[PDB]
Amino acid sequence: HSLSYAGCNFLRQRLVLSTLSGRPVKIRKIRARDDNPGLRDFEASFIRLLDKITNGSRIEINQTGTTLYYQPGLLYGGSVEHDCSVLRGIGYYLESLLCLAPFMKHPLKIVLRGVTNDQVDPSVDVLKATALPLLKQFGIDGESFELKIVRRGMPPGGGGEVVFSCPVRKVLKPIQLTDPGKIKRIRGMAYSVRVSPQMANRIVDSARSILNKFIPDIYIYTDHMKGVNSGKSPGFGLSLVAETTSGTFLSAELASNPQGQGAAVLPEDLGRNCARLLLEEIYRGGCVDSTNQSLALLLMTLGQQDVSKVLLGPLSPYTIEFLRHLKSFFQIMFKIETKPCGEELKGGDKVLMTCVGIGFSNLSKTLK
Amino acid sequence: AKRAITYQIAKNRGLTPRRK
Amino acid sequence: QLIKNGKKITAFVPNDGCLNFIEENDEVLVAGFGRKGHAVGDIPGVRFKVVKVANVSLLALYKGKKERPR
Amino acid sequence: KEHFRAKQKEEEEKLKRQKDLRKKLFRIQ
Amino acid sequence: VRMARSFHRTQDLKTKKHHIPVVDRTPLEPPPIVVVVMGPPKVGKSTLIQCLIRNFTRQKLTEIRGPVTIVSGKKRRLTIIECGCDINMMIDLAKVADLVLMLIDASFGFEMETFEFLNICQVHGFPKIMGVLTHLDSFKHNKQLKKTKKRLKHRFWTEVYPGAKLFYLSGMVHGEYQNQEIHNLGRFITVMKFRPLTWQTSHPYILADRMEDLTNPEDIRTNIKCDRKVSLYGYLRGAHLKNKSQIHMPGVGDFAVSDISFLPDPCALPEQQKKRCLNEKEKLVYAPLSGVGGRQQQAAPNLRKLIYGHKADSLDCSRFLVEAPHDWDLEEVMNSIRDCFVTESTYFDDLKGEMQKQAQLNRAEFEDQDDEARVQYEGFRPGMYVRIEIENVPCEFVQNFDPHYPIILGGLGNSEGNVGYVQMRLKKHRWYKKILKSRDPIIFSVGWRRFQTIPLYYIEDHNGRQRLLKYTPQHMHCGAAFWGPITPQGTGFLAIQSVSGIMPDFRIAATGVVLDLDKSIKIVKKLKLTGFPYKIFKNTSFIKGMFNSALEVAKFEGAVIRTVSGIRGQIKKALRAPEGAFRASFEDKLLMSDIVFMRTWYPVSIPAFYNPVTSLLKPVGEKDTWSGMRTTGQLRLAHGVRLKANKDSLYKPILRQKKHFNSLHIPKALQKALPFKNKPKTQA
Amino acid sequence: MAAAFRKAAKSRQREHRERSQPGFRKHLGLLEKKKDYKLRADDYRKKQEYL
RNA sequence: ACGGGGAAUCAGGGUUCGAUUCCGGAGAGGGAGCCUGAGAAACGGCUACCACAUCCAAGGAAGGCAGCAGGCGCGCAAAUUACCCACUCCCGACCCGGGGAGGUAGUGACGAAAAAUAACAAUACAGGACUCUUUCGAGGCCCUGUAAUUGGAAUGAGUCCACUUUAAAUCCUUUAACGAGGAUCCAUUGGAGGGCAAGUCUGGUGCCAGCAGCCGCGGUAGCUCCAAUAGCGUAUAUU
Ligand SMILES: Nc1nc2c(ncn2[C@@H]2O[C@H](COP(=O)(O)OP(=O)(O)OP(=O)(O)O)[C@@H](O)[C@H]2O)c(=O)[nH]1
Ligand SMILES: [Mg+2]
Ligand SMILES: [Mg+2]
Ligand SMILES: [Mg+2]
Ligand SMILES: [Mg+2]
Ligand SMILES: [Mg+2]
Ligand SMILES: [Mg+2]
Ligand SMILES: [Mg+2]
Ligand SMILES: [Mg+2]
Ligand SMILES: [Mg+2]
Ligand SMILES: [Mg+2]
Ligand SMILES: [Mg+2]
Ligand SMILES: [Mg+2]
Ligand SMILES: [Mg+2]
Ligand SMILES: [Mg+2]
Ligand SMILES: [Mg+2]
Ligand SMILES: [Mg+2]
Ligand SMILES: [Mg+2]
Ligand SMILES: [Mg+2]
Ligand SMILES: [Mg+2]
Ligand SMILES: [Mg+2]
Ligand SMILES: [Mg+2]
């Protein structure tokens, strides 16, 4: 029994849920009412990535490319190298790998080549700072569990390189994350490639000026990578991370415009805007940040049939559609209970998400 | 019509060393 | 990994081919080994041996006198 | 021939323990 | 001395208590315990069931068919089912039973059916077993009776744990067993406790109490052969069940559940029966088959409605844009955020405590919500009477229904409906007379399923190569690979050659565990290419017969080759005059009688053949007779094919002869140059 | 107790058997194994060292 | 840490054990109180409190296995919910009734005693045993060996009648008929060795070594020696 869907939006989650469920999916009418009717290259690049990290898959594309049929195989890890499309960031492909990595047959050692920092997709710095600690909460911690940035890449040239390694686990541990806690420290990451190193310092003194009043302890790291490590295009940006007493992480990031289009951005404006974007996240703060909500919900469903709870802020439209796809693929319905937080003055109202996992194990792992 | 167990089943000798 | 205290140790299986009876995540009974000493062809520094799996002695399984319950 | 072999077997037994073997090898060194 | 002696004894007793901790997922109100009664065909199985029912309920039932549920005690109910001699039922009941009553005829002794069922239980998860031996009224209360009891008990103690309880039924009074012996037997059933079995805990399953056909009558008049919709009633056991799921019914096939509904439970405990007002109905027996029984989105009430109650052709990004950013300069906006920032036990006991906290949270999480609300979030919990609606059932199931044969509905996990390549660790059974030949059909009992496939037997090498085997080894474990349904790792399996027919010997062929699942087999076979020397120049020899063209030799240049005698060589170049001949150098000189070969590895393949057993889709008298693909030996008997043996492959005495060598020849030039002392001296 | 394991395995005393020359090559002589070649190998080595 | 009579080990002196069938003390889930009686601070007597816990129509009512059996003490586990007052003794109004006190059988090689699994003859054919010896050698014979054959005596494990036993029985002891040549009516446990292919892996000193070998091209219709012997091993702690 295969599921049928229409459109090009939410393509990644449909393919990720299909391979974990083992049920085929049919996608129809991809960008039909467009001058270019076929699939985009970066979506085709994503499909090639799935074929390499799996074994036995069958993928069908029409001559026009308006329809896609995907029959998933079993997950096979090992050493993989992939050249990502420069249109989308590496983090666009990296989120899907974070969902599928613990269920491989062999531990995954993948090196990804493309663009690391971008305005559309989340930075690999943010995924390293926030997404990786979240998986450690589920028990996927390991010695080989790491993200390393070999060389940075900026659009349109790209030219970045990251290497990702993840252990394999038979089953996932349930979590009860209901207390967010108070923010202790703020850490940041300022980078400049193929430009003057003075750009990073002009970012630091702007973000620090806003955030020093709330918290005493802020320190922003500065990075300048030279030569082939710089990439093929100039740019600069800032990533900010907030750490709480309970161990949660809230993050925000911004990047400069690419060379080809857009007016030049003052580094002082970029520093101030990123700091305000972080404070917006704190007002919405939960146990997980808004970007990582869909990741947290998926790992809760894949538990060993136990009650699990997470406290998260306002639901994104991405997560709302993700919740509907979860009911279609895994037939799981969460129980939603909002928290008012009227006079606590913590900020906006939060949502408590609770569910019972379905019986799920790693079928790819070899018993020896 | 009754299937009685064999001598091998009744005494599970198994891999016992053979002696004189 | 010992159930009582969670320590991780290295033990001997008495014979090659008794490894086939043992699978991963199985429950085994472990006794001491090597107070007298270590024989030629034995690795020094290993002081434990596997005696039973699923409360059945390894020699009985090897000799074909018993079957391992699941 | 068998008598000669049995005499060496006793010497082999006379150091068959692991610590005994390492004992002489430091001493011969 | 007393302190040391007492302390070390208690530590040894604690070791018996230790085990691998697992979360307790049993319901607060458990379903009735499943009790199966088996034995040789005329041992007294049905007589014991009537005595047990009368012992607990003071009622006598006529024409018992299928499972019977009774109230036995304040807090326990039992489901009782009789097991026939047919091997198919023996396989199914072992997968579901919580308690097994095994009947032994003391006068005759042990029979094969007793030992076959014990092996089945060992494979699929060992339940609690109580042995009952009958027909003791034949003996005459002497040495012979006393020694027979000891002999049977100690042999029974090898298959189960030593010290296991046995029960003796001395004699029948009026065609019924004595009340005191039955009363004691029933008491031990009441207090028995059970371990969590791996397969039963993971998967939901149902033993069917009632079957009813839900089809339009005019459809049956139109075509009898039409697919039919069937409703099934039973208690839910094992794990939770979702509304839309795949379930396998052994003996029929795989199905998907259309509708599921919880129903008020019949044969409830008397305390719950007290709550509902009744006119002294006193329900204690339920057996329908026998006939006796029967900020707008932030709001929770709108957020839940929105989720579970243009966008397409748009960018897919997991980023939440801010539709209305705060000023972040006003003092009141700054005010709303300031509260965010800072202004002596065993490890076994501690791990057991953590397992208890998780188990308490699971039960108390949804207690406040209604049962209809609870079903949406956690599914149907075990212990509720439920109604199952199944569509597209074959018509032969309904028209050939037999109430004696149980109906089991086993829920399928994720991906268990798919097919793939299954790799198993396999050992031939010790009591089986024959060995298994690769590429011959065999029946596997795995998971919930019974099916026939074609396996490949292979062996592992230390370098990691899996090479094909002709036969299963007689005394060793062996790898087995076949194409079949996906099944989780660590589950046992059982092999039968023929489910139909009766044979005097042990019928279980082999036993093992599931190891790996994949889409590729990677199994390889050894292939040797053979040649013969025809021209010899010391180390170098010219070889013919290995290849048939000069293109063949070019592909294999530099390959390692050797003789039967063990001399190793290398291929150097191809010759011209014979089309396949080539030049090879060797360690030493060759003889013309030598044979050379090259060792190569050729990947193999297996056919994708999967034939499930469909015993329930048979006439009522013909449920035993199920057949499928025949093996190589059966096909040879059916036709006139006779085995012919190669003369070369047979082993024969060699009968070698004593070897002589020529005396060493010294050149005449060398003799002259030699010094006078060391010259060969011959007198003419 | 490794001796008990070895003694149980060695209960069966069948050893592997030797394969003979194929019939269509029977006129050539007996197929030589490693034991047969070792006799002619040491004989040639002995003479070469003497020469 | 209930005490003693006592058990083990010692040349002795001592040392270590002694809940445990005889004597003395103490208690009856826990601390207190009390009636009757010659005798009790009694618990198979009573009253209240604390902790547990059964039935209920919700008002009330009934409890104490460290007696004999029997169940439980996370899921992992070891004597029968047996027969009798025939013996020994105790209580009563009593020669006569009662007694899980006691007795009788059943039940895990945990401990102690005895003790099978064979004995006796014959025939044929071969020429080599055996001891001491660090590969050399020295002694030595009224026999040895043969997975070689042959014969008709003896007997109990068991099967099955009848006595005997005993409260009734069982067991032991008697005893009629069956019951042995691969006497297959087939003893085990620990330790140490040998034997092998067109087989597999690893390392090298061309032809070797290590580890090991029911897995080989085809094909699927029961070797030896040592210690003990109905017994024999392992781990932890210790002397
Ligand atoms: N004398 C004696 N006969 C018994 C005893 N137990 C069972 N039987 C016999 O068993 C017969 C009853 O057969 P069933 O009740 O049908 O037993 P079953 O094993 O289920 O046989 P099927 O129904 O054919 O499977 C009775 O007629 C008795 O003769 C026993 O303890 N003593
Ligand atoms: Mg019956
Ligand atoms: Mg005391
Ligand atoms: Mg005392
Ligand atoms: Mg007293
Ligand atoms: Mg008590
Ligand atoms: Mg008086
Ligand atoms: Mg008192
Ligand atoms: Mg009492
Ligand atoms: Mg008293
Ligand atoms: Mg008692
Ligand atoms: Mg217990
Ligand atoms: Mg008396
Ligand atoms: Mg009397
Ligand atoms: Mg007594
Ligand atoms: Mg025993
Ligand atoms: Mg013993
Ligand atoms: Mg004992
Ligand atoms: Mg004795
Ligand atoms: Mg009498
Ligand atoms: Mg004779
Ligand atoms: Mg070798």
Image (tube, rainbow, N blue to C red):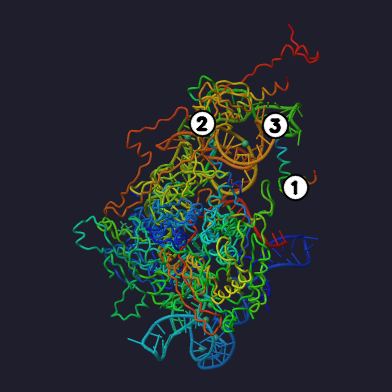
Q: Tell me the tag on residue D1.
A: 3
Task: Name the foreground residue: E203 vs E527.
Answer: E527
Q: Tell me the tag on residue E529.
A: 2
- Asked if marks 2 and 3 touch (Cβ < 8 Å), the reply is no
Residue E388 in the image: state x and y as whole percent: 33, 65
Q: Report the Cα–Cα distance between label 3 and label 1.
A: 29 Å
Query: Tag 2: residue type?
Result: Leu
Query: Ligand 22 within 8 A of label 2's CB?
Result: no
Residue corresponding to mark 1? D22
Q: Is residue G91 above or below residue E683?
A: below
Report the chain holding disc 3: D
Determine whether, in the image, residue G176 is placed left or right of residue A109: left
Report the chain holding disc 2: E
Report the chain holding disc 1: D
Q: Tell me the tag on residue A16.
A: none
Residue sticking out furthest to the top? E684
Task: Name the foreground residue: E255 vs F6.
Answer: E255
Residue located at (57% from left, 31% from top): E557
Residue sticking out furthest to the front? A263
Residue E376 in the image: state x and y as whole percent: 40, 71
Helix or strand or loop: what does disc 3 sit on?
loop
Q: Are marks 3 and 1 on the same chain?
A: yes
Determine whether, in the image, residue A348 is placed left or right of residue E141: right
Q: Report the Cα–Cα distance between label 2 and label 3.
A: 45 Å
